[PDB]
Image 1 (cartoon, each protein chain N blue to C red):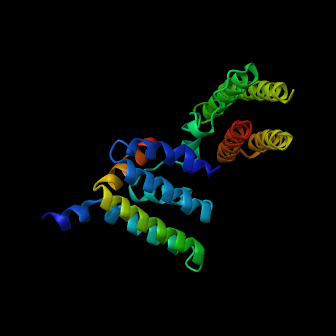
Image 2: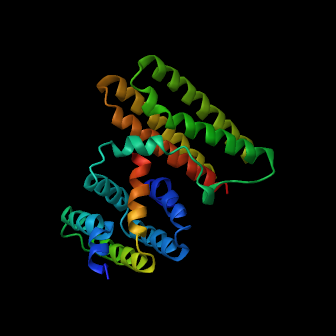
Length: 67
Length: 184
């Protein structure tokens, strides 16, 4: 359907993946930190699969706290 | 306990996500808890990086301080004894006053009043803890971070760097929450 467009527009692909990549780049040799980051992204993906759009809402509310 | 950025920033977001889907929300919460558990300071990095990627320009610790006065339910005391009700009131007051710092620090008169208010609130909170006692490790930690806040003020009036005051205020709020949780 609109599969590719939906996931392309989701904050998972738009925000989370690059952000986490950079977070790893902050300390590229720290194994446990990078593994924590990877597991976290995996779990966010699980949550997104369980409820499409929830990452968008997480991000939006997040920034709505900081305005 | 979890880290302050987690419970103060992310936890309320997780709660609001529950009406969307409870399972997925619980997944998010548990995941963040585990990630922060494994590598402390990570939640802050995540939040700041996300704020960066959305071009939200505001100081993280200042905003943290601004939003840090609300109750954390899972840590809060709901007991019928006078000592604990007093504990909750005093702790609440301290957290609120400390949260008002970013709004008052750019006006020296107001800020000079805020310092007196904070001293008063800390005195009363300590009174209340003493009333509960009739443990001491948490009291000592609280005293240490109060003193640290005082010293931070001393440094601030010299170098004028408010960010340090924001940091100390946040840590004192976290210690207040720790008092709450330990007495719970």
